[PDB]
Image (tube, coloured by chain):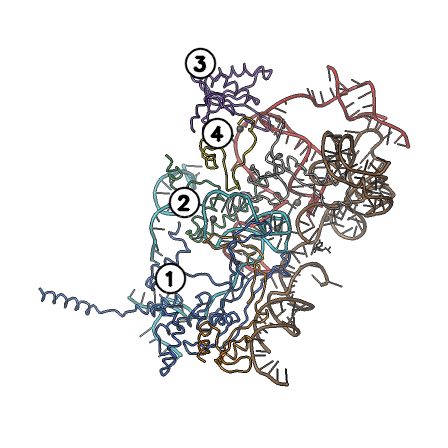
Chain colours: A yellow, B orange, C green, D purple, E blue, G brown, H red, I cyan
RNA sequence: UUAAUUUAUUAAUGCAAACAGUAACCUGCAUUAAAAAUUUCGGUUGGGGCGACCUCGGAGCAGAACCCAACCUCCGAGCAGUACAUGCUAAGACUUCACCAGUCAAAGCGAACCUCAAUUGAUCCA
RNA sequence: CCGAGCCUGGUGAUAGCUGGUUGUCCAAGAUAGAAUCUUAGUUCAACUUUAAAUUUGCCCACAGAACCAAAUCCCCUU
RNA sequence: GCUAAACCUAGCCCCAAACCCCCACCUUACUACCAAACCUUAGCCAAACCAUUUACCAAAAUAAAGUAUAGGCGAUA
């Protein structure tokens, strides 16, 4: 998902990526109400990143 | 006095609002009755010379019933206010 | 550019204006939005109606 | 939605590949979605009924139907059953063929 | 139809439109204020939040007060915020048992009190909570002048308050002359609770008494129009003599 | 089950269901065996293990519990270290 | 009412609480009474009542896969022994015609080198 | 119109009980059982209906099913 | 061809807005004239009985959320 957002320009990798930036590029939807404490990175696509 | 507690928990209201109460909210449970706990003492300053429970100008511990029925109605003693702490210690310094 | 909403174009009562709901929910919302300004026996009829519709929608029909 | 940047070698990591300029001379056209993706989707209508939808088709949807049938006849061993929607411009295919059809539409250049 | 205003607000509308509007400002301030009493029959949570058991999470706690009931004998005396607790109780301190009515009453005494400001011995129906609050207030005069309207919770107690407050605000010859230095000692001892007379006359009244006092102020037996018109004519003739 | 509350107009959950069963996101409900920690002295070891398992529920039991809860209990939860995160989804389930 | 639950109310005690002392009445908490007050009064049944039964197992009706009623015909159980692998796991199955429950079990790890006709009981509490 | 008056309100009480439930036309459609303060009811099953996916279903004779009648079960083939 | 049958506006309903109202008469009212208010709703009803419990009514949008929580831990809240 991260690489998909970077290649389609939805996340700028030239500036720090932060919860705001992932939300603003709409890669992760966080619901604080409903007890989301944030985002965990996931090894799912680690082969080609 | 009688201190009660509610058996059932009252749901919180808002920060400005008043809670909503029901039948289960006026089922009660006594927790304590301050009528009968061991009796305390109140601090009086005795302003005459009385029997050896106190002497003139002395702050003493007196049983509540005796202090409220004898020393204060007859003016024999006064309450241990900070004001008359200062006043009677000034009197003792003058003495 | 999105500074109004057609639900703000709706002219109607306050408790159903930009809302739909069913007959019980309409009565519940009318009681809590405009209930303290209602005439006394209109409230009494509204409370009777919420009470009846509660019993009806929660205890009758098929599909229990 | 930002139009995506100009990478050097395509397909990129994660496999994105832009629509082929100039457009292919075909009887039909398939638009990318707003997120610049191929518009082939899985669908499931009971616990059972699994379909693939191609759903931004412009032009000759019956030409597309014939080409999908030609392509998917080796993969199945029959002729797939399809539901053409000339109105909404979509094609339904019975069975899950999303990865195969996506690769096929990128091959065409859509 | 609907009322323009809600029915819980009808009373404020009266207090704005009537002779209740011509009541003085500070009195209507108190009537609108109407704050909360002191805990007497319930134990307050010392904190606004509490880690409740069974899960170590802080839930907010509010302390809700018991609906206490005060009889007219209480208002004839002084009970220290203490009244009857009319409630239910479970039969054997066990909810899976009968639930059954209960009335908890206070213990009532006929005590005799001297007030140094009024110089009078009053016999009243007190309880131990009043006696203890008097001891921690260092006298009945201080208790009544310091305690708030609803913590005092007596029509009689607030009559005593405005009598004492008017005594202070006018600095009356309270015992008699030949002791003006002792009177100065009294008013100096209680000099801190000094308010204007125009406020102390309205301290402690009910709204019925306040409206009655106000209309007694504004009765004003009508002025004859003979007087009004001869005043106007004399003014006009003096204007003509000037011109 | 309270399809329409008197307060909100909303549908209510049976907290008995939430105390006893676990809803996996695919629609499977997982329970304990009724009797799994009583009279273990007189139960045989194989029956004791059969009682110790966590089991799945029937289709009509699943649909009943689906009905008896609301959709808060049917969302997808991403807890930190979860012993059922692998069980929340169905793999190779053909038909 | 000699059924269940309660004494909130009254009563007479006791204990504190509020007075007088000397070298009674009011309030709070307990108890036993009275008056009550709330509440209920299973099922099958060749009408209902009386009488008997109510769970589980073996046999016959039901002769040869499975099933198959009875206020049908008969016989039994609410455990007992032996050690305490009477461990732990896990393919695949059976199932008392539903669910709950019940039953078997290869392989694997750890080891010595169960008998049993029913032989029993859920949930919440504690 | 008294084994506990009458009136209003709660109140559209509750009713596993009775009674009733209004155009046309086609189609598919029938009596296992288990538990239940349960047999005048309900829930699960079976059956019934609809839509869906997919590949085998039904009927058979040969082989086969224990010692202490009529017939059933199983299915390779039709 | 009798009895009839036909009719349309008298008004009403739900909203919005806006806060509304000479005499006699509590004695046997409508009669010219004589020595004191303030105290928990209960229960039907749900729990397929009922005995703790059982929505709201006693001003409070949308969402949080039918969540935390309560509960013969059950109906339900
Ligand atoms: N674990 C237990 C067992 C019994 N008990 C009590 O003992 C009683 C025993 O019932 P009877 O004596 O049959 C229960 O009703 C309960 O009051 C308990 O409180 N906790
Ligand atoms: Mg809020
Ligand atoms: Mg879909
Ligand atoms: Mg019978
Ligand atoms: Mg079975
Ligand atoms: Mg009815
Ligand atoms: Mg019945
Ligand atoms: Mg037919
Ligand atoms: Mg009931």
- Mark 4 Cα-neighbour bin, 10 Å: few <14, some 14–19, many ≥20: some
Determine whether the residue tagged by mark 2 lies in a helix, strand or loop.
Answer: loop
- Residue that carries the numbered disc 2 in the rendered image: C14
Inter-mark Cα distance, 2 to 3: 58 Å
Determine whether the residue tagged by mark 4 lies in a helix, strand or loop.
Answer: helix
Inter-mark Cα distance, 3 to 4: 31 Å
- Dots 2 and 4: beta carbons under 8 Å? no
Determine whether the residue tagged by mark 3 lies in a helix, strand or loop.
Answer: loop
From the image, state whether disc 1 or disc 3 is nearer to you.
3
Do badges 3 and 4 share one subunit? no
- Mark 2 Cα-neighbour bin, 10 Å: few <14, some 14–19, many ≥20: few
- Residue that carries the numbered disc 3 in the rendered image: D25
Q: Which chain does the numbered disc 1 sit on? A: E
- Dots 2 and 1: beta carbons under 8 Å? no
From the image, state whether disc 3 or disc 4 is nearer to you.
4
Residue A24 on image: x %, y %: 45, 34
E145 is higher (above) or lower (below) than G106: below
Q: Nearer the viewer, residue E189 or E4?
A: E189
Inter-mark Cα distance, 2 to 4: 45 Å
Dividing the picture into quadrants, the one containing residue I7 is top left
């Amino acid at each position: 998902r991260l690489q998909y957002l970077i290649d389609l320009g939805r996340v700028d990798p030239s500036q720090p990526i932060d919860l705001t930036q992932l939300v603003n590029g709409r890669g992760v939807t966080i619901q604080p109400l409903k007890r989301d404490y944030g985002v965990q990175l996931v090894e799912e696509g680690a082969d080609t990143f | 006095t009688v201190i009660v507690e509610r058996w059932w928990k009252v749901p919180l209201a808002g920060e400005g609002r008043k809670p909503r109460l029901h039948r289960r909210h006026r089922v009660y449970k006594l927790v304590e009755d301050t009528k009968h706990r061991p009796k305390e003492n109140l601090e009086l300053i005795l302003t005459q010379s009385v029997e050896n429970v106190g002497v003139r100008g002395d702050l003493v511990s007196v049983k509540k019933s005796l202090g409220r029925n004898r020393l204060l109605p007859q003016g024999l003693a006064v309450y241990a206010s900070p004001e008359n702490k200062k006043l009677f210690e000034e009197e003792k310094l003058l003495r | 550019n999105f500074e109004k909403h057609p639900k703000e174009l709706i002219r109607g009562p306050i408790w159903l204006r930009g809302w739909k709901g069913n007959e019980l929910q309409r009565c519940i919302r009318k009681r809590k939005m405009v209930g303290s300004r209602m005439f006394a026996d209109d409230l009494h009829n509204l409370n009777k109606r919420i009470r009846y519709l509660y019993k009806h929608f929660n205890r009758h029909g098929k599909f229990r | 939605i930002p139009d995506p940047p100009k990478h050097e070698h395509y397909p990129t990591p994660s496999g994105w590949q832009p629509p082929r300029d100039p457009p292919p001379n075909l009887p039909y056209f398939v638009r990318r979605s707003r997120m610049h993706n191929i518009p082939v989707y899985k669908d499931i209508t009971h616990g059972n009924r699994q379909m693939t939808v191609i759903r931004k088709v412009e032009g000759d949807i019956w030409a597309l139907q014939k080409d999908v049938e030609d392509f998917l006849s080796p993969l199945l061993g029959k002729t797939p059953v399809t539901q053409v929607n000339e109105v909404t411009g979509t094609l339904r295919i019975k069975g899950y063929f999303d990865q195969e059809l996506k690769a096929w539409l990128l091959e065409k250049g859509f | 139809p609907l009322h323009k205003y809600p029915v819980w607000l009808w009373k404020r509308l009266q207090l704005r439109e009537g002779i209740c509007s011509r009541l003085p400002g500070h009195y209507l301030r108190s009537l609108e204020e109407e704050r909360t009493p002191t805990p007497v029959h319930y134990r307050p949570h010392g904190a606004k939040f509490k880690i409740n058991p069974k899960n170590g999470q802080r839930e907010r706690v509010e302390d809700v007060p018991i609906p206490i009931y005060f009889p007219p004998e209480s208002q004839r005396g002084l009970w220290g915020g203490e009244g009857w607790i009319l409630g239910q109780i479970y039969a054997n301190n066990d909810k899976l048992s009968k639930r059954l009515k209960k009335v908890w009453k206070p213990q009532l005494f006929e005590r005799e009190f001297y007030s140094e400001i009024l110089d009078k011995k009053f016999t009243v129906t007190v309880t131990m909570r009043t006696l203890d609050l008097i001891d921690e207030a260092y006298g009945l005069d201080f208790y009544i002048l310091k305690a708030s309207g609803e913590d005092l919770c007596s029509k009689f107690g607030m009559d005593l308050k405005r009598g004492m407050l008017l005594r202070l605000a006018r600095q009356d010859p309270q015992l008699h002359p030949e002791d003006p230095e002792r009177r100065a000692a009294i008013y100096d001892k209680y000099k801190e609770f000094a308010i204007p007379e125009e406020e102390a006359e309205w301290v402690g009244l009910t709204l019925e008494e306040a409206i009655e006092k106000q209309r007694l102020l504004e009765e004003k037996d009508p002025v004859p129009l003979f007087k009004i018109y001869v005043a106007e004519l004399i003014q006009q003739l003096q204007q003509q003599a000037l011109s | 089950l309270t399809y329409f509350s008197a307060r909100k107009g909303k549908r209510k959950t049976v907290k008995a269901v939430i105390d006893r069963f676990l809803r996996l996101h695919c629609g499977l409900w997982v329970r304990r065996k009724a009797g799994y920690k009583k009279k273990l002295w007189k139960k045989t070891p194989a029956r004791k293990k059969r009682l110790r398992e966590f089991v799945f529920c029937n289709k009509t039991q699943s649909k009943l519990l689906d009905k008896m809860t609301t959709s808060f209990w049917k969302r997808r939860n991403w807890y930190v270290d979860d012993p059922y995160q692998k069980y929340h989804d169905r793999t190779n389930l053909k038909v």
